């Protein structure tokens, strides 16, 4: 699922920036090689996300995360909602 | 300050209202009403008699279409329940709501928890909590001479 | 209070506007006899102005 | 669907006679035509379901906390209902383990009290193998009761108390 | 009686003696929280004494959650050291315990109505606002939350002896009103 | 004994379903998720054995079809607007810091052209906006924003491309069209239904052509009983009977080219032992 | 039913939540505040103190001190004396 | 006046339009009158008999309620329309023995039960216990 | 937003843009415009392209809050996706809203 | 232990089935009640003597009791009671509203399943069940095949035999998950069918009140409960003190369980069924007495049968995903339509699709 999302994001970004590429005076071949380079180069555990609600009990933390991409064990995963619990 | 003074006067004259019945009239929330009530009682160096469950009986049962017989039945149920300590430490308004509910369910005119909660300003969950404590002791709380069409021997 | 005040006093318009308020429209019903009660309820006023 | 009302009416009409003899129950059965309660067009499935319900209700009425008269009347009701069935595989009365002690002591009291009619009825029911000795009265998924005051205080107890006094 | 209150919280304040840049502390501390749109202090938590410290830009720190005076002092010193390691000239000046909150159970239900009736000049019992009786003890400036379940919570004291004497004063009244 | 009865009664008041167990019999009370899948489950998934929920099929409601149409239109509008809108934003940003006047007027003219293009895109007709049933839309977004998750992205994509696109003739078939379909199927063979639909002239999907051919076919069922087939039916019935209940639907699928009605008639009229 | 008992007015809870959400305005650094003030000065010659606060989004006391350091107020006979962003 | 004029006056009043930019509208449609009621110290409502008003120096007034519909627009292509049914707005003094008086349709025996003279014609108001007649 | 330009996708985009800059085939202004467009596109996609819930349990080692960003560091963590388990010794969660 | 209501009318406290059966057999020991024999003037005297000895009464009294307590259809019914009156009104309504008045297919199916094997004597007389065998009327909840299974849960009830080794019910539970054929046959549909899932994945386990009885009979079987035990042993999940067994050294007679409480039965990786023991009863003489076939399907739900989406005359022999021809993504075809639509002339797949062999749950279960 992650590769599909990455490909869709690349396609959307390319389609959105095609107009700037045409306008500023750079040929669409530069755009195509940008897409190919990005796709080719696509091939510590860090989670970049957004927090919906970080509840803190006496010592129990409950994380409600709106969305995020995580990098667990060198493998990328995506989530549109995270309900996590931890004990400090 | 005006809302707190009105609440204090209503409490003093012997026809006390609830903080929710002053909030519904005033433009502030119950928290500020209570804070100003306490502040006024502290500054004026005066005190007010503690509210009893029988003070909210007449108004609650008059807002509802319950007959006078059901009103007296509910008042007696609530008074006996508070005497028997079946509701320890619970607000008198919740006890009044539970008594009104049981009296209405047992009497000909029946009322659901929703209407009683709206009239008394008590959440239906609180009504259930205060009703389950006095649920097993329903009959002995009723008046001895009480007529009804739905038996007091069976209730929800 | 507006309706009560006008009926209570017989002044018409707001209380603050008593300068132009018509007076005597509302009067205490005459209960001296039944005839006086009936007459008072059928009384017509002709303001001069 | 009204079966409980019929059972209650039959038990009431049996108790109002203040008798334990099976002759009165047989007379009531013939007069009320209770044997025709199973009569009526109904396929085997619903027929056996209704028979199961009737037997379960009769057995429930046969167990405490009902009075002795009601219990013996329910015993005759069970006998009549089981013996008069339209189902080829006659439905069996579900008997729980916790209730076996009560039924056995009730039978012992009946035979002790010279009430040989009810004792013989129960013996016939047992011999015919009309009992499914289940674990609980009903499958699990997902009046004239008896008071404790009579057991506590009665004529003989107070007579003994006043004699001692 | 033989039961004594057990302290649940101890609020103390100290003067670090130097102005602080709360942003730097938030960015460099291990467990600090800094939300200027919600409050004007840095909230730090530690595990060994299990206390929470609010650090203010003026250099005044407020430590709470400690269960003993020595524990509160040790936590305050720990926070001072943590701030010191961050490159600030923080010291330990004017350490003061500002509040002592303790709890206890007399182990018998209490009749709050009678207590408020006979102690109208001190107690304030409002079931609509709070299900507990608030007794404003006068000899020591302590406030007692007394509940029908028997639980008594003493707050507002600066010393443990104050809490102990307040509970000793209140216990006979509760015993006399034993439900 | 009475107090034990009372305790039983209160626990009756405090007592409490089957649904809490169904698929995740073991589940957490804080997160609500069951144990991780067994290695056997992973191996089964690797072999492409569809689970019960994967083979679950639900009919496409009319409101679902309208929602799909509206969502596709909105998706295409957004995808065609985002580029020109971004271009206009870039032109405005350049205008903000240009440090010139004639270049600023040229940028204003370019921005006016971009705004005209945006207006033209906005007023595009629905027919030209829908597409050609083969262009890649954001079908996965429709499964989440437009649909609340009741339909997967692939299901929506297939339904839109193959069935619900306006370029698919959903009108009732005509006698001449049916005859043409039959003739084309006979001459071209019944195995290349894509080319049959293409050659049919009218805009039809291969699935629709095959469906119409089958519903009007006559070789679908054998239409004549044989002794071997009768013996097979008798054996199957005797094997799968449970009494007077003879489930003919289950019998059919061991018979070749037969329907439940045919078996019912055959076993009731001829092969009945009585 | 008029004035049926309720703990909180629906508007009152919403306002309390909104006030807690937006939060109080913070004291930004003088350089950033100064840059915003000077940048906005180009749009119009003069600004009202209340209106200027919304644009800068700074505390009134803090904003006034910064404005006093450079800006001055001129008495206008048409509406009232208003602040002028030009220090001179 | 009670049946028609009061309702016409409320209906003919222009809707209240307020702008912040959220926009607020208030429209008053239906007018209700209850029987003359008196509220005790405890706040319990009870029907007010004309003799009790005379004896206790009360005003024979009926509560007045109006159905108010409020619509709010916040320039977010959403409209919220909330209606407050039977909003208390005041009390109208009631002319005795009129259609809205408690002594309406009561038989002469019923009036005597209420300590009212059947020969009493009504047609006046009790304002603070004083029987007030409106002179034409 | 300056949040999602740290993962594999955002990083690789950063180096690709840098490679074009050093190749004199694109201007830095277009580079940063493309970066902002990528941020908007990735935000929209993740918010609208993704529907799958994960649940993670761990022992929160440390946390931090400043300028509207939470920085949790958890130890001995286990993530639960739709059906599979992912166990890691340590993880960092950077949240911003 | 004595079975008693743990919940008012919903559940029973955990008890050993062995102790319960021993109690029942000891309370009926030598009483002539557990016979399992078919029901049978000289015998009248013996019956009278038996009644006299059992009731402590005279022979004449026994004869009087026997003669007087004797037993005491026809379509017409008159002088109706309340229940008989209700039945009469219902019959009249059915007659006036119905035109055929026959048993529906579901009713006959249910009756025949319930009464499929009653009074069926063994053919060998060596598999005869002993007098008292603790029949368990188990029921297995069907999996979520159709969406509505979540709302109302269908179940298949089986009369398992007490003192019967486990893995005899596991091998008897008929579920479609055991007949699944793996792999994708898109390239060519004439491949030799891969071994059904019953053979590839032999592992399975019961879970009855905190005890995982794993089916480790075969070498291909391995602990499925290991994952659950490890998952519970993690940080904290409420569940704990999980036990393990082998499932072939235990019998239903040696099990400690509750009645009406949902227990688990997992197989084929994650196919889970809810096992509920409705009741436990001693074997009677009017029910099946065999042991070869006693794990007997007393009731099944008669699930729906999927039909080919092209033609509604045949079922689904194939399921296609990502199909370039089907309207729906998961599309169901029979052999004929699938072959006509997915292969030009020799098995070369046309377009793109992933086709798998689909076994109809409503046909094999
Ligand atoms: Zn299965
Ligand atoms: Zn087909």
Image (cartoon, grey):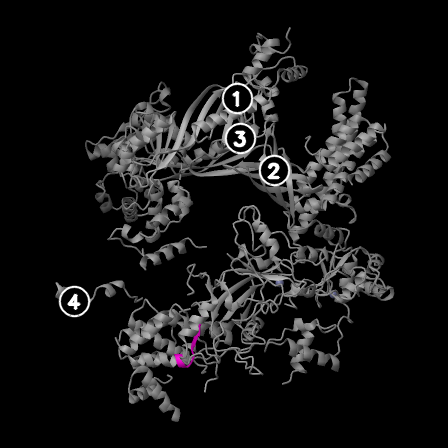
Residue G39 located left or right of residue J132: right
Residue marked by disc 4: D160
Residue marked by disc 3: E45
**Residue under the point 38% across and 27% down:** E156
Per the model, the C-alpha gap separating discs 3 and 4 is 78 Å
Per the model, the C-alpha gap separating discs 2 and 4 is 80 Å
Per the model, the C-alpha gap separating discs 1 and 3 is 15 Å
Residue H70 image point, x, y percent: 50, 35
Residue that extends furthest to the top in the rendered view of this protein: G88
Residue F11 image point, x, y percent: 40, 55
Residue marked by disc 1: E56
Q: Is residue J241 above or below residue E28?
A: below
Q: Secondary structure at mark 3?
A: strand
| Image depth: mark 2 or mark 1 in front | 2
Q: Are marks 3 and 2 on the same chain?
A: no
Q: Secondary structure at mark 1?
A: loop
Q: Are marks 2 and 1 on the same chain?
A: no
State yes or no: discs 3 and 4 in contact (Cβ < 8 Å).
Answer: no
Is residue G50 something one can see in this rendering? yes
Q: Quadrant of residue F102?
A: top right
Residues rendered magenta in the picture: D126-134
Chain name for mark 4: D
Q: Is residue B137 above or below residue H3?
A: below
Chain name for mark 3: E
Chain name for mark 1: E
Figure quarter occupied by ligand 2: bottom right
Between discs 1 and 3, the one toward the N terminus: 3
């Amino acid at each position: 699922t992650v590769p599909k999302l990455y490909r869709s994001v690349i396609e959307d970004v390319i389609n959105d920036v095609r107009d700037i590429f045409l306008d500023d005076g750079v040929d669409e071949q530069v755009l195509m090689e940008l897409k190919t380079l990005w796709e080719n180069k696509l091939m510590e555990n860090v989670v970049v996300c957004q927090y919906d609600k970080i509840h803190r009990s006496k010592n129990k933390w409950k994380f409600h995360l709106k969305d995020g991409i995580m990098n667990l064990n060198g493998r990328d995963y995506i989530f549109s909602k995270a309900i996590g619990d931890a004990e400090w | 300050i005006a809302s707190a003074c009105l609440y204090i006067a209503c409490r003093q004259e012997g026809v006390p209202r609830t903080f929710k019945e002053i909030c519904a009239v005033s433009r502030i929330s119950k928290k500020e009403i209570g804070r100003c009530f306490k502040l006024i009682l502290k500054a004026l160096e005066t005190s007010v008699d503690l509210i009893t469950t029988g003070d909210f009986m007449s108004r609650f049962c008059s807002n509802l279409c319950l007959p006078k017989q059901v009103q007296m039945a509910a008042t007696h149920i609530a008074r006996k329940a508070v005497e028997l300590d079946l509701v320890p430490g619970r607000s008198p308004i919740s006890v009044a709501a539970a008594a009104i509910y049981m009296a209405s369910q047992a009497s000909a005119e029946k009322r659901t928890q929703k209407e009683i909660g709206d009239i008394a300003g008590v959440a239906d969950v609180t009504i259930r909590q205060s009703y389950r404590l006095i649920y097993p002791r329903a009959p002995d709380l009723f008046p001895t001479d009480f007529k009804f069409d739905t038996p007091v021997d069976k209730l929800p | 209070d507006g309706l009560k005040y006008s009926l209570a006093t017989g002044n018409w318009g707001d209380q603050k506007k008593a300068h132009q308020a018509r007076a005597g429209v509302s009067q205490v019903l005459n209960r001296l006899t039944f005839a006086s009660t009936l007459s008072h309820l059928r009384r017509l006023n002709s303001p001069i102005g | 669907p009204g079966l409980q009302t019929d059972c209650e009416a039959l038990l009431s009409r049996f108790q109002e006679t203040d008798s334990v003899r099976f002759e009165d129950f047989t007379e009531l059965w013939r007069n009320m035509k209770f044997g025709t309660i199973f009569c009526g067009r109904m396929r085997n499935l619903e027929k056996n379901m209704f028979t199961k319900e009737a037997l379960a209700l009769a057995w429930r009425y046969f167990l405490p906390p009902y009075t002795f008269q009601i219990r013996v009347g329910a015993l005759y009701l069970l006998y009549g209902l089981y013996n008069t069935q339209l189902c080829q595989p006659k439905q069996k009365i579900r008997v729980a383990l916790k209730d076996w002690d009560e039924v056995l002591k009730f039978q012992q009291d009946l035979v002790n009290a010279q009430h040989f009619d009810a004792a013989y009825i129960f013996r016939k029911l047992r011999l015919d193998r009309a009992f499914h000795f289940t674990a609980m009265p009903k499958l699990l998924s997902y009046k004239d009761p008896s008071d404790r005051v009579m057991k506590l205080i009665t004529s003989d107890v107070l007579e003994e108390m006043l004699n001692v006094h | 009686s033989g039961i004594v209150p057990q302290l649940q919280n101890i609020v103390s304040t100290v003067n670090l003696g130097c102005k602080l840049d709360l942003k730097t502390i938030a960015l460099r501390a291990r467990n600090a929280e800094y939300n200027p749109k919600r409050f004007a202090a840095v909230i730090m938590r530690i595990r060994e004494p299990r206390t929470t410290a609010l650090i203010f830009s003026s250099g005044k720190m407020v430590c709470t959650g400690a269960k003993s005076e020595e524990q509160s002092r040790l936590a305050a010193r720990k926070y001072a050291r943590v701030v010191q390691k961050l490159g600030f000239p923080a010291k330990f000046l004017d350490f003061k315990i500002q509040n002592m909150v303790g709890s206890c159970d007399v182990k018998f239900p209490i009749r709050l109505e009678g207590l408020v009736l006979t102690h109208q000049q001190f107690s304030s019992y409002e079931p609509e606002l709070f299900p507990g009786l608030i007794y404003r003890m006068i000899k020591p400036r302590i406030v007692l939350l007394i509940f029908v379940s028997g639980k008594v919570v003493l707050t507002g004291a600066k010393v443990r002896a104050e809490i102990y004497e307040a509970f000793e004063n209140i216990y006979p009244i509760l015993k006399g009103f034993r439900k | 004994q009475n107090r034990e009865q009372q305790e039983e009664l209160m626990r009756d008041l405090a007592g409490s379903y089957m649904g809490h167990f169904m698929k995740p019999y073991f589940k957490d009370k804080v997160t609500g998720v069951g144990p991780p899948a067994n290695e056997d489950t992973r191996e089964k998934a690797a072999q492409g054995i569809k689970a019960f929920e994967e083979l679950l099929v639900t009919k496409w409601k009319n409101w679902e079809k309208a929602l799909l149409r509206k969502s596709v239109v909105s998706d295409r509008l957004q995808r065609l607007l985002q580029p020109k809108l971004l271009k206009l934003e870039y032109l405005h940003q350049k205008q903000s810091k240009v440090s010139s006047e004639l270049e600023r007027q040229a940028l204003e003219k370019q921005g006016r052209e971009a705004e005209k293009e945006i207006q033209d895109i906005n007023q595009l007709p629905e027919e030209a906006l829908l597409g050609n049933r083969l262009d890649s839309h954001d079908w996965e977004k429709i499964s989440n924003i437009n649909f609340e998750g009741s339909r997967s992205a692939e299901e929506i994509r297939k339904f839109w491309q193959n069935s619900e696109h306006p370029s698919i003739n959903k009108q009732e078939w005509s006698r001449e069209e049916e005859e043409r379909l039959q003739a084309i199927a006979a001459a071209h063979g019944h195995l290349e239904w894509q080319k049959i639909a293409e050659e049919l002239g009218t805009s039809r999907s291969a699935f629709q052509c095959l469906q119409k051919f089958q519903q009007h076919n006559k070789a679908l069922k054998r239409k004549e009983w044989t002794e071997e087939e009768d013996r097979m039916l008798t054996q199957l019935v005797q094997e799968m009977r449970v009494g007077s209940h003879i489930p003919y639907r289950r019998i059919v699928y061991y018979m070749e080219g037969r329907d439940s009605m045919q078996l019912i008639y055959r076993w009731t009229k001829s092969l009945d032992p009585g | 039913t008029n004035y049926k008992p309720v703990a909180n007015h629906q508007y009152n809870i919403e306002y309390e939540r909104k006030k807690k959400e937006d939060g109080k305005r913070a004291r930004a650094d003088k350089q950033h505040v100064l840059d915003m003030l000077f940048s906005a000065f180009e749009k119009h010659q003069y600004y009202n103190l209340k209106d200027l606060v919304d644009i800068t989004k700074q505390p009134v006391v803090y904003l006034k001190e910064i404005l006093k350091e450079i800006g001055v107020q001129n008495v206008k006979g048409i509406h009232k004396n208003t602040w002028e962003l030009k220090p001179e | 006046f009670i049946q028609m004029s009061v309702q016409r006056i409320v209906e003919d009043a222009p809707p209240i339009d307020l702008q912040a930019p959220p926009r607020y509208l208030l429209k008053f449609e239906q007018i209700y009158l209850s029987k003359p009621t008196h509220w005790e110290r405890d706040g319990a409502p009870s029907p007010m008999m004309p003799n009790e008003a005379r004896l206790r120096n009360l005003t024979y007034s009926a509560p007045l309620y109006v159905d108010i519909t409020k619509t709010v627009i916040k320039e977010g292509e959403e409209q919220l329309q909330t209606q407050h049914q039977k909003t208390f707005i005041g009390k109208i003094p009631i002319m005795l023995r009129s259609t809205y008086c408690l002594l309406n349709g009561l038989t002469d025996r019923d009036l005597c039960e209420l300590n009212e003279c059947p020969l009493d014609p009504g047609g006046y108001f009790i304002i603070n216990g004083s029987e007030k007649v409106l002179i034409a | 937003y300056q949040l999602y330009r740290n993962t594999t996708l955002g990083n690789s985009l950063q180096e690709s843009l840098d490679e074009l800059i050093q190749s004199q085939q694109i201007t830095p202004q277009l580079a940063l415009q493309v970066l902002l467009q990528f941020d908007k596109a990735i935000n929209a996609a993740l918010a609208q392209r993704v529907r799958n819930r994960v649940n993670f349990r761990g022992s929160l080692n440390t946390y931090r809050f400043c300028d509207n960003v939470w920085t949790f560091v958890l130890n001995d963590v286990e993530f639960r996706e739709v059906t599979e388990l992912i166990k890691v010794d340590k993880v960092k969660i950077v949240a911003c809203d | 232990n004595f079975p008693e209501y743990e919940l008012p009318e919903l559940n029973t406290r955990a008890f050993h089935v062995g102790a319960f059966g021993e109690l029942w057999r000891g309370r009926l020991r030598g009483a002539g009640d557990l016979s399992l024999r078919e029901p049978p003037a000289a015998d009248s005297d013996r019956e009278d003597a038996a009644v006299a000895r059992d009731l402590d009464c005279s022979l004449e009294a026994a004869a009087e009791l026997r003669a007087v307590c004797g037993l005491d259809e026809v379509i017409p019914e008159n002088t109706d009671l309340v229940t008989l009156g209700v039945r009469k009104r219902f019959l009249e309504h059915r007659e006036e509203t119905i035109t055929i008045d026959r048993a529906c297919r579901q009713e006959t199916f249910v009756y025949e399943m319930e009464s499929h094997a009653i009074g069926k004597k063994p053919e060998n007389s060596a598999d005869m069940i002993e007098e008292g065998e603790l029949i368990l009327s188990v029921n297995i909840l069907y999996p979520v095949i159709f969406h509505k299974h979540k709302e109302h849960k269908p179940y298949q009830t089986m009369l398992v035999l007490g003192s019967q080794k486990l893995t005899q019910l596991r091998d008897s539970i008929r579920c479609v998950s055991d007949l699944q054929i793996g792999g994708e046959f898109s390239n060519t549909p004439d491949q030799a069918p891969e071994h059904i899932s019953k053979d590839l994945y032999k592992s399975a386990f019961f879970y009855f009140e905190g005890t995982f009885y794993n089916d480790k009979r075969y070498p291909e079987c391995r602990d499925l409960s290991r994952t659950i035990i490890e998952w519970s042993e993690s940080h904290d999940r409420g569940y704990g003190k999980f036990q393990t067994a082998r499932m072939e050294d235990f019998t239903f007679n040696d099990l400690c369980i509750k009645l009406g409480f949902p227990y688990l039965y997992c197989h084929q990786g994650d196919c889970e069924h809810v096992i509920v023991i409705t009741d436990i009863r001693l074997v009677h003489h009017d029910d099946c007495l065999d042991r070869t076939l006693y794990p007997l399907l007393i009731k099944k739900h008669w699930l729906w049968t999927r039909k080919c989406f092209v033609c509604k005359m045949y079922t689904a022999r194939w399921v296609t995903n990502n199909d370039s021809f089907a309207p729906e993504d998961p599309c169901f075809f029979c052999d004929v339509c699938f072959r006509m639509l997915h292969y030009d002339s020799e098995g070369n797949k046309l377009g793109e699709f992933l086709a798998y062999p689909y076994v109809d749950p409503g046909t094999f279960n």
